Image (tube, rainbow over all chains, first blue to last red; front, side, top):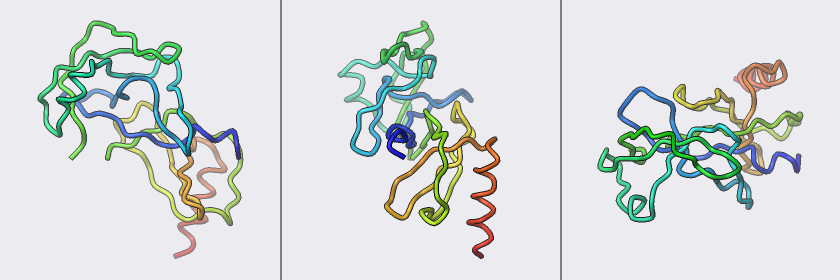
Amino acid sequence: YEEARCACPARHLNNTNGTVLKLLGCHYFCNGTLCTAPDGYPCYNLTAQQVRTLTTYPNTSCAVGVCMKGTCVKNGTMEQCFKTP
Amino acid sequence: GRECCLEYFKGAIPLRKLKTWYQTSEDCSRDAIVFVTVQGRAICSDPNNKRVKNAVKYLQSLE
């Protein structure tokens, strides 16, 4: 299984609503490879400043997006997001 | 943390290479069984696939 390079689980960001877990951006790391989320995958589009504010509690208003060719394209919805624990 | 699978591995994993398994969060966009090999790789798998359910039964039957 070499083609299973990008088939490993990745950590997602949490939210306060009951909505789907979303990836930070549209790329993730697997088995020594930089991977790209599939088109349509739920994501957050944060600025570098916002990423620096990410804590384990809702202290960030995060722009919800949809992955398109490796880019998290915003849909206009905001969500309080944060890292687990 | 909150681990979710973005891609399934559609091939077959030799059972002799499997160490354990777990299921990702119910809040993940895609439901997945994650298999952990002896080498330490985590491989995302489709829970609807019959081979996946049979692999879990095998790992459970080792108890």
